[PDB]
Image (tube, coloured by chain):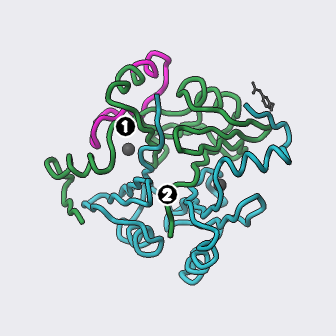
Chain colours: A green, B cyan
């Protein structure tokens, strides 16, 4: 059977600024870097940044809702979000439609999110404030 | 401080075939569905399918290398790949790197992968045979 996410690979247009974003700004751990990529971890997540000449810097109105959310604790959430804001990190969404979340963009316009809470906690919240037509299995 | 991947959200053009693909073909657990999305899990992975009229069914030549790899054991790899093949699921790349990998497309052209092997395994292989320009930290 499938047993989780083995890795997330993001295509990047400029490797050095992307490594700086994920390692310096977001605090992920850099394990290795080469001419065409980098390997980082964020807790158990294996993140690969892959230099791709096809990657375009994409404004958020031009891309669909596909996005990648990173876990953060309730105690750290607000100050991390505020630090990203003060650093000039672009955003893509304001309405909290799935709980406590901050929506921000990477240098290439990959849609990212800080989120507080597990799937179990989101299902429990949705039982009280369900999305239209929601059914639970 | 970020502690891991909280969730992966894929924009989908048609909810029913995407639910069938992830739940029935790929065996993920469906926890909830609503008029415009679904929540599934795959091991620790929280997957959200979000119905989005902006999602284009995208040929693999027209998207960049961004992709999502799921873990599977070596013992299960070949029969799962054969299941995808029987279902006519398209392949977007052949494997040329360490660890078994099967590169396949979802109904909207999201680039997926089955991979056997951890970051630690990849780093160990890279230390013995470093990529061009590779530096370790
Ligand atoms: C600061 C840093 O880690 N620089 C670096 C590492 C590996 C390769 C290259 C050149 O592609 C630069
Ligand atoms: Mn989200
Ligand atoms: Mn991969």
Left or right, A50 with respect to B20, comes to right
Q: Does the magenta stretch include residue B14?
A: no
> Which span is picked out in magenta?
A82-102
Q: Does the residue labelled 1 lie within 8 Å of ligand 2?
A: yes
Looking at the image, residue B1 lies above or below residue A115:
above
Point out the quarter of the image occupied by ligand 3.
bottom right
Residue B104: x percent and y percent?
60, 67
Q: Disc 2 marks which residue?
A: A4
Q: Nearer the viewer, residue B126 or B34?
A: B126
Estimate how packed mark 1 is, as few (under 14), some (14 to 19) or many (20 or more) residues with alpha carbons within 10 Å.
Answer: many
Q: What element does badge 2 sit on? A: loop
Q: Rounded to the nearest whole Å, what is the CA distance between mark 2 and mark 1?
A: 19 Å
Q: Nearer the viewer, residue B35 or B43?
A: B43
| Residue appearing at x 29%, y 58% in the figure | B36
Looking at the image, residue A1 lies above or below residue A43:
below
Q: Do the residues labelled 2 and 1 touch (CB within 8 Å)?
A: no
Q: For mark 1, name the chain.
A: A
Left or right, A92 with respect to A57, comes to left
| Residue appearing at x 36%, y 31% in the figure | A73
Residue B112: x percent and y percent?
57, 61
Left or right, B85 with respect to A104, comes to right
Estimate how packed mark 2 is, as few (under 14), some (14 to 19) or many (20 or more) residues with alpha carbons within 10 Å.
Answer: some
Residue A44: x percent and y percent?
53, 44
């Amino acid at each position: 059977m499938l047993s989780g996410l083995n890795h997330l690979t993001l295509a990047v247009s400029q490797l050095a600024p992307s490594v700086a974003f994920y390692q310096q700004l977001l605090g992920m751990t850099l394990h290795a870097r080469w001419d065409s990529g980098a390997y980082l971890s964020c807790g158990d997540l294996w993140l690969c940044l892959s230099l791709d000449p096809q990657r375009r810097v994409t404004p958020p109105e031009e891309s669909d809702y596909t996005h990648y959310a990173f876990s953060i604790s309730e105690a750290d959430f607000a100050s991390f979000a505020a630090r990203l804001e003060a650093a000039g990190v672009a955003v893509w969404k304001l309405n909290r439609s799935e709980g406590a979340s901050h929506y921000f963009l990477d240098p290439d316009g990959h849609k990212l999110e800080l989120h507080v809470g597990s799937l179990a906690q989101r299902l429990a919240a949705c039982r009280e404030q369900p999305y239209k037509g929601m059914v639970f299995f």
